[PDB]
Each structure stands twice: as structure tokens, then as C-alpha cells.
Image 1 (cartoon, helix red, strand yellow):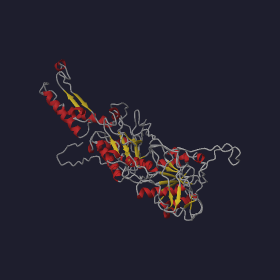
Image 2 (cartoon, rainbow over the protein chains, first blue to last red):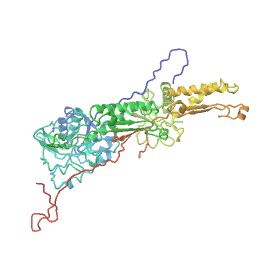
Image 3 (cartoon, rainbow over the protein chains, first blue to last red):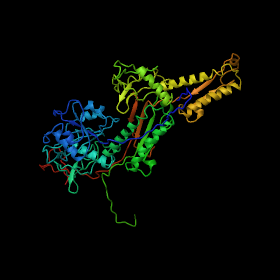
Image 4 (cartoon, helix red, strand yellow):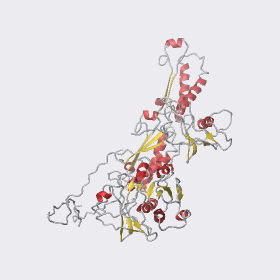
Length: 354
Length: 202
Length: 50
């Protein structure tokens, strides 16, 4: 540590491992632009902040082209900054980017590129757009066949039609803004459904309630439905996967933003020597992040011993021989809240029975 | 030994700087600031010099095994940082340059102390001083966190005495034998994170 | 399970078998229509809701 050579006063500042977890950039999307759009440069993530910032790329032509309408509809719903890449070089740019967590298809049919991109380790929940044609109720078995069931996706059926820019707006770029608006206003764990679309755009296809019955099961297609109380609202929080674990886009995107806020904090404690002083700081810094989500109501459970658990230590999670290979193992439990998809009400006339 | 791949390029002195002289200063900066047992990787280079060759992460996958080559990699959070603590040997004992250079600085600080007790006659008064003086050094490293283990009976052990480490016939040849155990800490090379949705299971 | 190749942070999500039993569609009938009824298409389960 310190060497003492000459008689004098030696100042040395020993400091413990200071570890804290930063939460930032929950929903920052990317837009796979149309390949024909000549204004996006080839193989460069040109980044835009606002619509006046985007308008320096192209000063006119808000009316016709389907990318140009989509990013205008994106900034109207929710505020964010988005990168614009061509779909030809989509798989080359996205891994070398800072925070891209919604690979949003602005009507470009990039299902194969999404499956190559997102492994279970990376993250970046990627929304899709529904089929622009009519979906009847008895043609449900074929309309689901085009999408392949993966828990990193979401489909939204009715393509939207607005007053300005008379071409049909894709629903995926519209719903991309509602994600960043909900994750900013009420946090990431609240489901992005049941929020009115702030832009003045109506669904082109009306939604029967029985039509949503046989589509919102299996690899579900969420449906934008307009009714009289709140206007045109999004009405689906299900992803493209039907099992008990990963059924919901709030329960999926909470496990993205927790597994990315901790991974940035683990870069500070990267090459620290792992013993009992080190993994007490890593346990206490992660458990304060998972406690702050529990006080905000993002995790279910009555008290904090049930909402989460974190376990580091020789013995408990890793053996001695794994320490000799230099790999410390952190087990993290989360009980994420799931939305009330079907609130049911049971009415009894037996009040003394209880 | 230790190898560091990308030769560095700086603004001043436009010839290519070798990485070995650059990494030599980071060793003396880490060993002074946080001690010898902390791994000399994950420290930004204070000089204004960038790597001449960019490092792909998959390129480091098949080079950081076997007789490994450590790689200086620049990323956006901390700048150009050193990113390897492995030596040129792939076995379980001597895999790391902190676990190697701790066994150099302990086996040289004690060897200078053994010159004072060099020709002392070895009996029960002598090797009680040598046992108690070495065990206080290995206790001071344990309180600084340089040695793993829960309590001091597990972090180290030192054994001198007729019987235990040396026999009677080796005393008659005049050679006393000191056995010293160390459990040096090894760096977290691959921190892995396992996420479960079963919180009442634990 | 997991392979460790390069020094870094590895996220792997191990999840237990989540199994739950869904109860739905207890009594959904089919109607063998009359063979003379020309409006039902041949060999196709035409489905009606209301």
C-alpha cells in the first residue's frame, strides 16, 4: 500500500467501493426507416431530438411518406429522442449503440432482423405493427401465423388514420411514443395500455369486443380500441408469448430496465477482488435499488423479505472453485406486478355470511 | 509474465508507444493507491494516449484464454482502460497478476526480515519470535482485505517447531523450515447475474 | 449453462417452470346442420357468434 522512505507527512486517501445504481433512459426507441428514403445516410444512426430538430433534415413533405408521418406521430404522443437507421444495416448498428431499448418497426417488415438481434441477455424489447388489412374473427388462425412467438415483441392491430398526412400511420410508431410517455409519467412497471392517444388520430378499423376475444390469447395481438369515455385508447398489455412467466409488456420491460441499470453499476465493481468486504457493498447497493422500486409500488408483496432477495457469498450462491476461476455470482429475485387484465366483480346477497 | 495487445498511439511523440512501459506505470500507481492485491486492470490511463487498434469484444473472447493476452480496451464511461489481469499461465493456482504479485511482495518482505534472524540459534525462544513476527504481517494483510476467508484461522497459517515442520536431524544440519499459507484474493473477472421471478422460493 | 469467455458482466435469467391451469370454454357446442341446407359450405366449420 504505502511506502515510507523519507521523514515527513504522508497523505494517502483510502476509499471504500462506492456503488450506486442509476436509472435512466427507460424507453428510447430506434426507427427502422424505409429503404427508399434517400435522406437517411447509409449505415449511420442519425439521431434526432425533437420535430424542429428533425425538420432540419427535411424541411417539407410531412404529408406522404410513411416514415415521415410516423416520426411526426411519434413526437406528438410522447417525448423522446430516437435514432434513425436503414433496415438494410439494422443488425450492424444496434449492437454498437448506447441506449436502444425499443427496436420499433415503422411499417417495414423486419421480423427476421429482430429475432437475430435480441438474445435473452441483451434486452431491447421490440414492438411490431399489426397487419394493415382486415382481420375477421374466423380467420384468426391464419393471421397469427405470420408472427413467431417470442417474449420480446408486441403487435398492435388497427393501423391508424389521421387528419393530417392522409396516408395510413403504422401503429407501432404511435405506440412507441406512448411507451416513453407512460414510463416517464408513471414509471416502467405500469402497463402501457389504457392511455388515450394525445395525437388527433383515430383507428382506421373499428374493433368489435368479440373480435378481441379470440385474438387476445395465444401469441396475442393487442388492439387499439376507441370508446366514448376516453377516446381512442390502447387496450392491450400482452406480449407475443402465452405462458405464466412473461405474459405482459410491463412484466417484460421491468426485467429489461432492472437488468440494464444494474449492469451499468457492475462496470464500476468490475475488477474488484471478491471477498467479504467487496460483495457486501454489491449486495447493499443492489438491495437499495430493489427497495426503492418496492416503495414506489413496482414490486408486489407485503414486506421487503417477500418482494425481492439478493444473495452473494462464498457458500450460498457460488462455491470455492468458482472463486478460483474468478467469477462471482449474484442471484436477484423480483416479484413484478402484473396489470389487472380482467377485473371481475362477484355480487352476493349474503352479507351476514361474509 | 503478462502481455498487453494494442500498441498505444499518443498526440505528442507521434511514434507508437509500446504498451508494456505504459502498463508499468499503472502497476506502481495501483500498488501505491489500493495495494498490491488489487488487480491492475480497470484503471483509466492518465496520459492522453489512445489505443492504435480498436478492440472487438468477440476478439477478446478467444484471446483471453490459454496463455492469455490482456487487451487494452477503450469504452465511453472511463476512457481507455486496461482490461486484463491474467498472466501468461492457464492453471488454477497462478492465473492472475494480482495473485502472482502478492506472492512476490510477501516473499520479499519476509526475506528481508529473515536476514535479521539469520544466524540466531534455533530453539523454542527463537522460532516463537519468528512465528509471531511473520503472523503479524499476515494478519495486517487480512485486516486490509488482501486475504480471503472469514476468520484468521482460515486466511493464513504459519508453522515452525521441532516436530511439526522439521525433524530433529534437520536441526542438526542447521536448517529451520517455515511453512506459510496464503489465500490471496482473485479479481472478479466474470461477474454474472442470475435473475429469478421466484421470490418466496429463495 | 453459461459460458464465460471475455471479462465482462453476464446477465442470464434462469426461471423455474411456471405452471398454471386455465379454465375456459366449458360448453361450446357444434351443430350438425341438415344436409339439404345449401347455405353451409361443404366441409368447413363456419363459426357464428350471435
